[PDB]
Image (cartoon, rainbow, N blue to C red; front, side):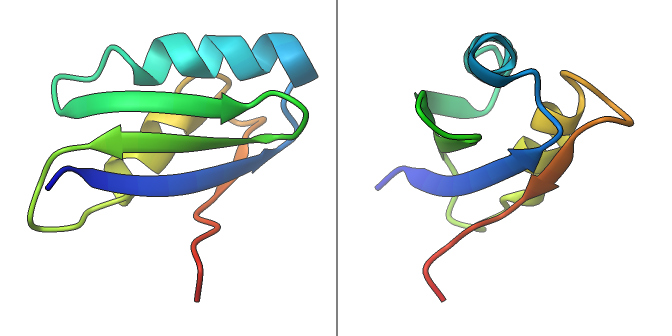
Length: 77
C-alpha cells in the first residue's frame, strides 16, 4: 500500500548524476525505495502516503543539481 511516482530530468550529468539521485532520494524521511533508469534520464521512486503527493520527490531531485535539473513527473496519463 506504498506510494510510487516517476520523474525524468533534462540537463543531468548522465550515468553519474543518475547515481547521486539514487543517494539523494533514498535518504528522504518519507521514502520507502527507488530505482533509477540507468540507460535513460529518469527515476521510479517509491514513498509512503495515502495523500499521493509526488511534488516532494520532484523537489528532492531538483535539489541534487538545482538550477540545472528540468525534473518532470512522467506518469501514465
